Image: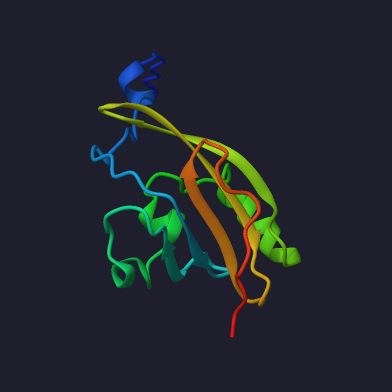
Length: 138
């Protein structure tokens, strides 16, 4: 005879999955991903010190591993629906709240040209480079 109902609200209950990456670590570069979201390659900029390992990132997920907490249809659904057709076109900016303070970053994803690969650019929200060149595969 378990008929004990309980209805209440707790701010702590709703407030969960906070920022875990206390570290800042600033960097801007592109990363190759697969249809499933697996790291294929890593290409960072040539104007800063080395941070994360190039091989350590490979084999793991980008938004499912490197980006813990983004596991949702808010950012995943867009990637899935895009893969189903073979061309994920998304352009927006994400806010990365840290202990040191809030930091917004612009990320642009687009299907690779060679095919069977995706291109995800990650860099702080700021217009710097737009017209590139000398980028042709062998």
